[PDB]
Image: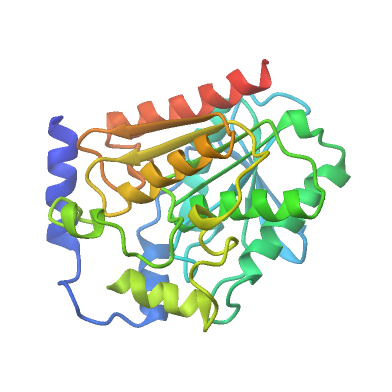
Amino acid sequence: AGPEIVKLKKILREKAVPPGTEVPLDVMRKGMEKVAFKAADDIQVEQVTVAGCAAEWVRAPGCQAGKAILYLHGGGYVMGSINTHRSMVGEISRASQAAALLLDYRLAPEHPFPAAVEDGVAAYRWLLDQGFKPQHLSISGDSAGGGLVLAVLVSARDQGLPMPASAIPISPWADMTCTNDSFKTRAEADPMGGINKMAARYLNGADAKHPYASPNFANLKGLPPLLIHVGRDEVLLDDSIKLDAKAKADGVKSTLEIWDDMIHVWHAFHPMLPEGKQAIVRVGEFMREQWAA
């Protein structure tokens, strides 16, 4: 294990709330806002309204005309924002050489399932109506947003929408049931259930096996080529392994990368984690590969 990830895990545990204490949602929300990384100063930003939602066009230098990424942020479907993810999305824009549409989709419990999926699908539809070709598009997202990526694709496909050139779920949460073995077998090495409460907030009585809630139970047939990033040291490991397997069986060209010693959305720690930078570079490279094909 690299020195950076070791020290990163140390800091995270030293700074985290003990297991089982209930942090109010508005407290978690504000805490996530305050620890959010400042985006690099060469990242340009433009506010837009997309499908009734606030959003930002996130443009790193080197962005190609005609291309775009719909980005869906993490936050367990109950938190996160444009601000919390602007830094990581800028670096994805940089590696992929394409501007990114960072969507402030509707959150639970104010807006429970399927609000987030509706916003994702409509935002993707918005991109199309703006004149972006399907072959010039990609959809990416982390954690809850990584599951949201797959749900948006499946929903859009059921509604007759054309598929984009690629999709890259990062540490996706694709199973609301949280019954996978890695929740037990990787729990020791994961410094990042509170997750069950978030699932309860998002679902609000809905079936946890609903395809648009938990894409690991969805029909993935027809989906674009997948790059799935996940850390070996996270409780959501099996979500990614099972997603890959599901995609394979449903005909989808899927590529699963389990990064050793890595934690949940390690990409977000790119300022101090070389593997975080590396994986972001990989994401952008995969996007460009699928566009040049």
Q: Residue at x 53, y 61 (%)?
A: 81
Q: Residue at x 19, y 37 (%)?
A: 261
Can residue 91 be seen in this snapshot? yes
Q: Is residue 89 left or right of residue 1?
A: right
Instruction: Give residue 281's position: percent from left, percent from top.
Output: 45, 25
Q: Residue at x 63, y 70 (%)?
A: 114
Applied colour scheme: rainbow
Q: Quadrant of the N terminus?
A: top left
Front residue of this view, candidates 137 and 210: 210
Q: Residue 211's quadrant in the figure? A: bottom right
Q: Is residue 190 above or below residue 114?
A: above
Q: How many marks?
A: 0
Instruction: Give residue 213's position: percent from left, percent from top.
Output: 54, 64
Instruction: Give residue 100's position: percent from left, percent from top.
Output: 64, 40
Instruction: Give residue 43's position: percent from left, percent from top.
Output: 56, 37
Q: Is residue 54 left or right of residue 79?
A: right
Q: Is residue 199 above or below residue 133?
A: below
Q: Is residue 162 above or below residue 115?
A: above
Q: Is residue 149 left or right of residue 187?
A: right
Q: Is residue 269 left or right of residue 102?
A: left
